[PDB]
Amino acid sequence: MIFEDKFIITTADEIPGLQLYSLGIASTISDNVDEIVENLRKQVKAKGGMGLIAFRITCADGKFLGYGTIVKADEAQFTMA
Amino acid sequence: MIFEDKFIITTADEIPGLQLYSLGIASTISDNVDEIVENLRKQVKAKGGMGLIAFRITCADGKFLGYGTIVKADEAQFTMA
Amino acid sequence: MIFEDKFIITTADEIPGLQLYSLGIASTISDNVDEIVENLRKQVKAKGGMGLIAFRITCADGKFLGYGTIVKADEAQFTMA
Amino acid sequence: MIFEDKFIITTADEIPGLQLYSLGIASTISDNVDEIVENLRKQVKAKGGMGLIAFRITCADGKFLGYGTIVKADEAQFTMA
Amino acid sequence: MIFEDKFIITTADEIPGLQLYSLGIASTISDNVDEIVENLRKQVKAKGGMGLIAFRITCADGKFLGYGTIVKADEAQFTMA
């Protein structure tokens, strides 16, 4: 219970010192940040991502697509691939 | 000696030269900058945060939460132990 | 060192370590994220760009839309002649 | 006497190379950008600031607002020792 | 005369490595991106600027607000005193 369990979420940051690799873009429309974040977490967690960068929700009119990009750092120790 | 800052509010991207650590996301809806800022300052410090980054107010000219990530930097204790 | 792959899309406009060259600006409006990405792809793939930076979407009838700056790395195959 | 910069205005950036210190946030409701800039300028120079950062200001529609943060740069920090 | 690059358009993307000088701010209200860009380019090059920062688009088929900061690189460096 320690590997593949560290989920981080930052907004308007860069987390310098880490090499991030693009794993695609995630988007989900819904209400309550807990459901949006919880739904995104399961995406990286299940895709082996690390978290979401620039998690800006900023709604306008019913549009709650928490746009975020999934990133991953080398040295996964999960699968040599 | 006695510094000064307590709650820092900046409008940009981040504060370089300091190690910022995210301990959660903050979100609030309301009017008046005094109540919006105080609402976050209370939610930010209540969780141990010391400043807010990217202070927004309105953009879609209607429904819009300021949205802000809570962050904090270590004082001198090493995370090793 | 991991080099570039094919089409990359991030939300932060950075990717340090690479020389980005402006090839202009792209803009598209539609009610489909997969169609917008594909529509822009044909626009970038046709311009030999690298990918889309800061790609956001949020509109119902015809309000906001998708937008981004095109970028390319290496020589622009154009200097004088 | 001897004045080249002093007043500096950037649209969403950070002006790297300069130490900026926040001494409060400025906000004013009005129409016409000429009056907004002049209104903040008088508020910024009146406080002995340097200029204004983050000039996003959304388009007009019925009740928008151009919020901004006041900043100032100077040799060393606050002495008053 | 090695500057080569002169007119550059960037959307939500800083340009480190270049010394930018503020020459004021531009603003455009109307529809049609071709008229907005042409209005800024003519306003930027007419003042002998370098390029424009910001941009973005919103509310198509209608009026919005196209603005940006006018910058210019020519302050040169400084002698190592």
Image: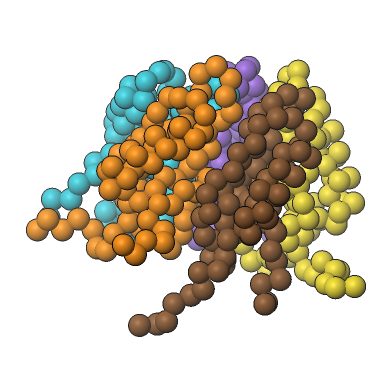
Chain colours: A purple, B cyan, C yellow, D orange, E brown
Q: How many numbered callouts?
A: 0
Residue E55: where, in percent of width, then height? 65, 42
Residue B54 drawn at (x, y percent) = 45, 39
Instruction: Tell me which residue sits at (39%, 37%) in the image.
Output: D40
Residue furthest front as drawn: D1
Seen from the viewer's position, the closer of residues B13 and D3 is D3
Relative to C36, is A16 on the left or the right?
A: left
Q: Is residue C78 visible?
A: yes
Asked if C74 appears above or below C69 in the picture, the reply is below
**Where residue E23 sits in the image (x, y, percent)?**
53, 54
Assign the C terminus of chain C to one quadrant of the image: bottom right
Residue at image point 52% right, 60% down: E21
Is E10 displayed left or right of A31 in the figure? Answer: right
- Residue at figure coordinates x 70%, y 66% from the top left: E5
Front residue of E4/E40: it is E40
In the picture, residue D81 is in which quadrant?
bottom left
Give the x, y percent position of residue E30. 70, 30
| Residue E77 falls left or right of residue E13 | left
Which sits in the foreground, C37 or E20? E20
Q: Residue at x 85, y 57 (%)?
A: C48
Is residue D12 left or right of E44 when viewed as pictured?
A: left
Quarter location, residue B7: top left
